[PDB]
Amino acid sequence: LNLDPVQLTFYAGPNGSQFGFSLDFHKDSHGRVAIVVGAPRTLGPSQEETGGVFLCPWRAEGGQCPSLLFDLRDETRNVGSQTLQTFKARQGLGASVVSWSDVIVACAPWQHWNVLEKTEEAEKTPVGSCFLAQPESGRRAEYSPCRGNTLSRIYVENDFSWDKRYCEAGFSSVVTQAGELVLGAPGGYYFLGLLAQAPVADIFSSYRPGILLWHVSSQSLSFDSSNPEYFDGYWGYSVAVGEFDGDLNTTEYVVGAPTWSWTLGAVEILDSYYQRLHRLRGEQMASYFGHSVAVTDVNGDGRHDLLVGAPLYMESRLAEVGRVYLFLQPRGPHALGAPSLLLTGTQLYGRFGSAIAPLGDLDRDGYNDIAVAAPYGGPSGRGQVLVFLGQSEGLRSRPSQVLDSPFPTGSAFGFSLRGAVDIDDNGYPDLIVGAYGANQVAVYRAQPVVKASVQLLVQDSLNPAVKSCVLPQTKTPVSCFNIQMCVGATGHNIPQKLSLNAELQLDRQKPRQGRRVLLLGSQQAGTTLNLDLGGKHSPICHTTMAFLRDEADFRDKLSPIVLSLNVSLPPTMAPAVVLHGDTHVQEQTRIVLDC
Amino acid sequence: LNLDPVQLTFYAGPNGSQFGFSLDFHKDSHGRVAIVVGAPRTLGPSQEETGGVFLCPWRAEGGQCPSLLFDLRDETRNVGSQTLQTFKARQGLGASVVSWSDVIVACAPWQHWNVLEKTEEAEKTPVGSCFLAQPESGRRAEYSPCRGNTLSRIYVENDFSWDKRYCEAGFSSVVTQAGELVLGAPGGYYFLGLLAQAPVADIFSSYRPGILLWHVSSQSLSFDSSNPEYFDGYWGYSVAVGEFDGDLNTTEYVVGAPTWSWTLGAVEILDSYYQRLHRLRGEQMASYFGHSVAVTDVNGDGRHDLLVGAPLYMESRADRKLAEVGRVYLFLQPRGPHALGAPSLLLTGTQLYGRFGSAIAPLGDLDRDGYNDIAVAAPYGGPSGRGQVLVFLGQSEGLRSRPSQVLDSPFPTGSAFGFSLRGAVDIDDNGYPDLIVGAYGANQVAVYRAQPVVKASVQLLVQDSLNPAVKSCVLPQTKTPVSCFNIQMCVGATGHNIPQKLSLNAELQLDRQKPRQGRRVLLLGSQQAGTTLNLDLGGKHSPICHTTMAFLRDEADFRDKLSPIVLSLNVSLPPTEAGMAPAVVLHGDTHVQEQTRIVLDC
Ligand SMILES: *[C@@H]1O[C@H](CO)[C@@H](O)[C@H](O)[C@H]1NC(C)=O
Ligand SMILES: *[C@@H]1O[C@H](CO)[C@@H](O)[C@H](O)[C@H]1NC(C)=O
Ligand SMILES: [Ca+2]
Ligand SMILES: [Ca+2]
Ligand SMILES: [Ca+2]
Ligand SMILES: [Ca+2]
Ligand SMILES: [Ca+2]
Ligand SMILES: [Ca+2]
Ligand SMILES: [Ca+2]
Ligand SMILES: [Ca+2]
């Protein structure tokens, strides 16, 4: 709602693009936050297809960020017969970035790995990897469960089972609250999908430079499945962490399979033991249900809620426009299955739902908020971010704000969206929009929100011929009533330069020269006053006095008086304020005399 | 707790005018708050003590104030045979000022009134008169419920039954939320005392300038009692309103009778029909149990609680058998309303002849923690006897038994600092209720502003027990290896209206039990086991935690391997005394200890 569109933070990257495929907020232990962006198609050791990650300090003007190296070299180790080796060709370092407690985990899902066992070989297959690093410490603990030495003949022998040659671990990187790192591998089990879990502390403990194999304590890998629906399931395409079970103190992983059950799609909730507590499938085939998955409690009830993206949805306008499915967390026995809000974009081929970013209390509204992105939406397919507030009792169905791509067509503005981290540390979380091949990363800063609570004090009714008030000049006896207005500013971090303007309307329904009551001071049927609330918490109530003419004067006495007070922000750069809540009170006064 | 004692506002009246005897907060139509101060001995137009009320607008420096021009003039109106007279000489206009909505009720209890019929009369007795005003419109009105025209001999003929000649109505004035003015006349019904309650709108709409004896049609008065206990009860010395019977439609009055049942003292809680719901007897005779009464929900359970004051309570010390200090009783209302019984808390003063409990002011939520705080004033307490005010914070069970803050008189001795108290109103509009204390001896009022309360939080994490020499990260500036680990402490500062310059200080003491310079655990850097560093939180919802590398001495080097390794994290405000007064109050947990041990084979 309060995300500043007119001013944005622009971060540049390599001319080879991909700067913005994935990104996250690196929360420093000191309390600072900086944006870490993976560019999975930067230059290699010698102009090679590789990845790469940049670390941008949080700023406003922006610029060329420094680069954080993880691993770019074709290693080769001779374990007896097996001369195993790694290949950086199109590794994609930066396709998944997640940060936690001074550690950054950035993945290269398409990194290759071949083991030469004399004549036979393991084939140069994309096992993928995800490299961990504490930039302050400098320690690098690369993690790659799918790296192995089992030669291809063994795979071919029995049933091509328990394979990890092309798992592509790290297609989606997330980290729990405790620091446990979770990685997706869509290609695991012969292009079926597996997951990896390992403590970052344990990963750093068990890692040894040079050697290209380990087990790293009790790292938890997903179970291989022979179910036909899982074939080419593409599990671990997108992952997130949130609390969903009946017990606390445990972190669940939500994983998306956009091709589950013959491109139908699914999303699953897993514990650390991978018990599959809940699984919700898609509705439209080839709609890519699960491309991006987000976890946040926008309802404000505390219990986390689920958002699932289907950018390839074909709306029954059969127009290819994505859709975000919302799932509030209920208190039923087997609840959470039925979706509640189905948000759908407008621009054709917009891919509405490629990036769902939790935002938390974006506008100090008391409920969490979200930002969905359609990378090819908008007027001319540029791509647009749709901010949806909590609003309680569900989610804001309408876009509280629409952020337009300032990038040319095809930049896919809005592929990776992250929020839920107050970058301004002002109770107002910000948003970051990165896009694959964008070459630029945009950051939206939220602005203070002012809720208004408005009340009126007007006499309910009176005799038009009371004749108690006295006109100054003419000295005529007239009836009159007490008109007062009190508007107060609620919310957090309200700016002290507030200049709210209140406009009063007496007999609003009646037109001009059809009006009945009329102000003494200004001789007008309505005025605006600077009812500024800046610099104080108490409401301002400056009254007025409008006279009511004699019976014989007018004839609109049969019409009851309408007293509508409407408060609006001043019209006079960036407003830095968003009026919300009650802003128009129309308490009424009727005319009562005999009939 | 957070009431600033350094920067005070001083509002002055005329010399010897008793400016500050009673006071209340008047809210202007625009929401601007002003103070109504009674000065019950201000010089009248004819150089005589009559009374007066000042309307002090809120400022920073303070000073002189304008006064509400009432009608200070004796009145004489002959209604045919009789001759009604009102004498406004030493009437005490300002002895009880209470502001409700846009009206101010300033009562002169000692205004005299006579009815001259031929030779006879009704005796020139003090009936009292409250003066209602609307300073934004000039609408003046008067209310004298106890005025009568019955000749003196009639009461003698009927045993002084329903004798309302000595009411001094306005001795204690309150206004309910529904706009009903309730006056306690301690001297009504021949000093038994009564309550006179009438709607303010009816008071304004039944007053005609010139008529002295009229009758408000909707007013209600108490019942004269033949029970010997009530005699000379002064029933109406102090009066307050609150909810005590269940139904929120009915409003109940709490009325003090400080000399009920032969100076024993009592407080009666009774509904609008003056049916006694409950009676709270005194504890010690001549203690004036009922001198001050306040109603507020200190414990926050949603039910109003009662605060009684006995300024002349003589406590039973071990050394002194009976010493006059004063005592405030706290009664907590439970469910099942007609069960409020034994007192829940018994606060007692310290200074002799300090009159602890002469004023009980509900402060609202001064600390902003969901519980109601009060102020009890001893006008002659304090080591020098010049006057003290004690702030008591509310909690789940009763309220704090010790004064969170103590305010001392800035005025010379005998100023009666604390006689009049009034609070629970944000005067400067900074989100925190303020307090106004009236020292009529010095003819001044002190305004205390509540500075913001910074609620702190501390979380010092030490990962686990460690081995003496793990031979990890080397000792600083040496290739010599030692055992190293991380110390991380997150400190947060949450509060309302906190300034942008807040910067706490974290004292990190490494095994404070051991003497410094040779502690078992030092830092991997400067090696100083005690490091106090500033951590700024000037508008940061995210606690900031600068991790530190810490070194552990050799197993042979440190010989006490059995003593617990206890790290100390202390949070303190910076030395703001160098500049102006401390702008914040760092209430809350600011000091924690975290203990670990020495592990082996790790
Ligand atoms: C989580 O809370 C505490 C702290 O870790 C722990 O002792 C407790 O067993 C946990 N609760 C669960 C697992 O339900
Ligand atoms: C209080 O008064 C309201 C008037 O609207 C009434 O509806 C309600 O029943 C009353 N409650 C009682 C008498 O307990
Ligand atoms: Ca859980
Ligand atoms: Ca929920
Ligand atoms: Ca919000
Ligand atoms: Ca922000
Ligand atoms: Ca009641
Ligand atoms: Ca209570
Ligand atoms: Ca409190
Ligand atoms: Ca204040």
Image: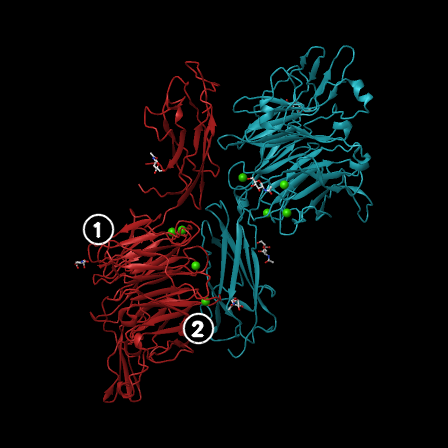
Chain colours: A red, B cyan
Nearer to us of marks 1 and 2 is 1
Q: In this rendered view, identify the residue nearer to me: B407 or A414.
A: A414
> Which label was assigned to residue B479?
2
Element carrying mark 1: loop
Left or right of residue B393, residue B328 in this image: right
Is residue A171 in sight in this rendering?
A: yes
- Which amino acid does the dot numbered 2 rest on? Lys
Chain ID, mark 2:
B
Q: Is residue B33 above or below residue A244?
A: above
- Which amino acid does the dot numbered 1 rest on? Pro
Quadrant of picture, ligand 7: top right
| Quadrant of residue B140 within the rendered picture | top right
Q: In the image, residue B123 lies at what x, y percent?
A: 77, 18
Query: Mark 1 sits on what residue?
Result: A379
The quarter of the image holding the N terminus of chain B is: top right
Q: In the image, residue B194 lies at what x, y percent?
A: 72, 30
Element carrying mark 2: loop
Chain ID, mark 1:
A
